[PDB]
Image (cartoon, coloured by chain):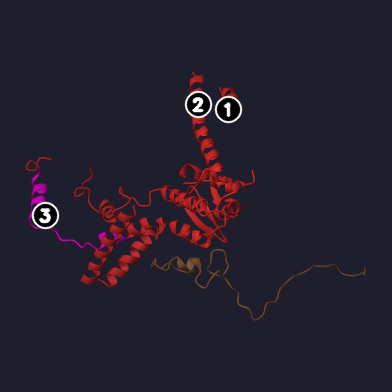
Amino acid sequence: DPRHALRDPERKFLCDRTLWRIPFSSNFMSMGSLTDLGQNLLYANAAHALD
Amino acid sequence: EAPRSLGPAPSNPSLQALFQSQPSAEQEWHGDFGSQPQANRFGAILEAVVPPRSDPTHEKVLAIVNALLETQAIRRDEAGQMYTALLQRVARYNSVNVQGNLDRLIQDVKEALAQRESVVALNAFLSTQPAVVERGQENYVAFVSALKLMVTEAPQSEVYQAGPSFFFQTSRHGSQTVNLSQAFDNLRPLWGVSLLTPNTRLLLLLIAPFTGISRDSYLGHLLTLYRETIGNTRVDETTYNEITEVSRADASNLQATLNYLL
């Protein structure tokens, strides 16, 4: 009712018991255990680095 | 129509490897030694007297990967990847037996490519098609013979199954596909006997130039009229070309002649 303080909404989510999944496939889908970008680099014997 | 491999000869992967990874002084595709400087003369003389032995492993693997590129087992942009993988495997398991097997494989793939440089689908289609009808087993037999003759004599024609029906296509990148299953299903009630669908009409128009059919039957009459129409079309094409070329010493003239001509 009036005679009350104004608003300031704040939103947050709470996700429990779940791992954040970032799949290696280009389209982020899972069309098979061996992703297409996993088939790439399979016989390329390269190194790269992860940062 | 892009060149599958870099070599000037699409076949002979060994020759393609020769073209790609050999100096352009040993190859042949179709001076005055003694006046050359001392360094060049002595180098050539020493190389001739004691030839330098080299490993024919990279050349063999390049020939193999060129053969794979020609066979389309390996795409164009992964040729280097497959080349490096094959080199790694061969170096891991290098032996005289492995080199002999590599040479044998190159010879066999070259022979197979040279020899190589639809019918089974038609056989399956004929097998699934009934071979006995109650309206004369001679028009059907001769029509089947004509169909086989035309599919065999066609340079680039495909017969394939698409679900529950068999299709006939006049060319790889064309726009003339005939549903053979439905065409024969329509033709079956009237072998030995306007009422034909465009699919079977197109089939008849395609098979008419390549056909034993008795002229008394309805199919015989239809084939004779289609042959006459096709001959009229060819002679009309010749007349149209002559008339147009003469009249060009206007697109309106082409309009007028086509309208009067069809």
Q: Which residue is mark 3?
A: B47
Question: Which quadrant of the view contains residue B73?
Answer: bottom left
Report x, y in % for residue B122. Answer: 47, 57
Q: What is the letter of the red chain? A: B
Amino acid type of the residue tagged 3 in the rendering: Glu
Q: Which mark is residue B239?
A: 2
Tags 1 and 2 both on a single chain: yes
A8 relative position to B40: left or right: right
- Callout in the foreground (3, 2): 2
In the rendered image, the vertical position of residue B255 relative to residue B41, given as above or below: above
Q: What is the letter of the brown chain? A: A
In the rendered image, the vertical position of residue B169 relative to residue B260, given as above or below: below
Please name whichever residue, B44 or B114, is drawn nearer the observer in this view of the structure. Answer: B114
Q: CA distance from mark 1 to mark 2?
A: 10 Å
Q: Which residue is mark 1?
A: B261
In the rendered image, the vertical position of residue B61 relative to residue B177, given as above or below: below
Dot 1: chain letter: B
Read off the magenta span: B36-64
Report x, y in % for residue B103. Answer: 24, 64
Mark closer to the chain start, 1 or 2:
2
Task: Name the residue rendered at 32%, 66% in the picture.
Answer: B86
Mark 3 neighbour class, 10 Å CA radius: few under 14, some 14 to 19, many 20 or more: few
Report x, y in % for residue B22. Answer: 24, 53
Mark closer to the chain start, 1 or 3:
3
